[PDB]
View (cartoon, chains in turn purple, cyan):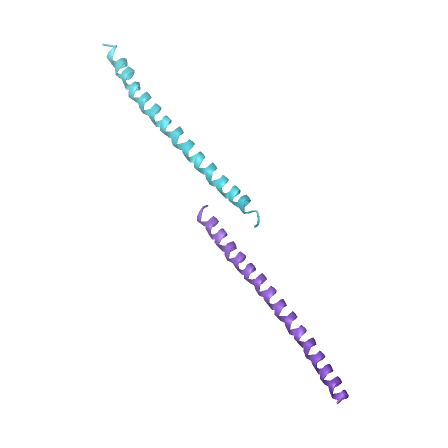
Length: 57
Length: 55
């Protein structure tokens, strides 16, 4: 019929919206986790430099 | 006379023919309209399925 087609269109539009939001959230999560692991490496490096300075002291 | 007993029938079949012709003309026209509507509905269903054809 006709209204069934409208329902089919609507039931896919929200699917597209959800997929777009999912992609955005995935990108943001990956970027944040990469920054966090980089800061972990930074903290390890800072600990090593503190240890070396304590050795010189 | 013997004329009238048949002429009565002669005129009688005139209205018979008129009713039959107008009725059959209406019948064929409405039948064709119904067939066109059914064809439209069937095509609507099939082509609505095929316009979908997954998205």
